[PDB]
Length: 148
Ligand SMILES: COc1cc(CNC(=O)CCCC/C=C/C(C)C)ccc1O
Ligand SMILES: [Ca+2]
Ligand SMILES: [Ca+2]
Ligand SMILES: [Ca+2]
Ligand SMILES: [Ca+2]
Image (cartoon, rainbow, N blue to C red; front, side):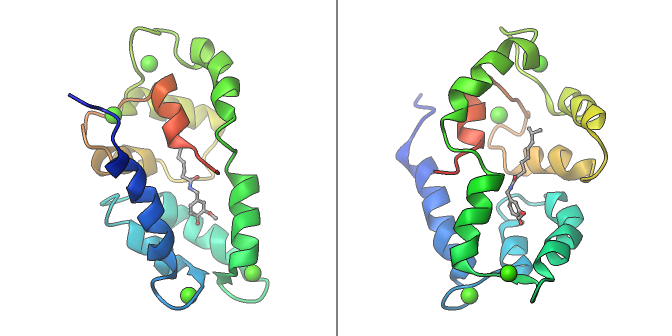
């Protein structure tokens, strides 16, 4: 009956130590690839794999913690985006009473570009999602992103 639970939040908290679990403190593609299990199959990493090494190839396909927070901070917007996404609810979600499915989401992602994989969302939304029915909405948008 309860959709929001503390357990769900703990997942993100635990994942924090999961990345460094490999060693004392290090962020590498191997660590990220591990998360693939919780997501079953998230190409998002496959395509990015090259992107990570490219920008990370400055010294090694690994990123230090001091830079990890900065990178995630800029890449991921704080929870304050909730208000910003609020305006996007009407435009992003025309139906309003309805939610965007994975199939419809793909069409939107296509218009954006093709830098990332096309399957990332199709499979990521399939496993990582408890419902498995794939659905995106304003309420979920806030939980989707959380830099802090
Ligand atoms: C540094 O590159 C990395 C960035 C992230 C951050 N992860 C994300 O941004 C997940 C992608 C969000 C998918 C959005 C789908 C919408 C259209 C519904 C994780 C690991 C990394 O290696
Ligand atoms: Ca490490
Ligand atoms: Ca680095
Ligand atoms: Ca929709
Ligand atoms: Ca869902």
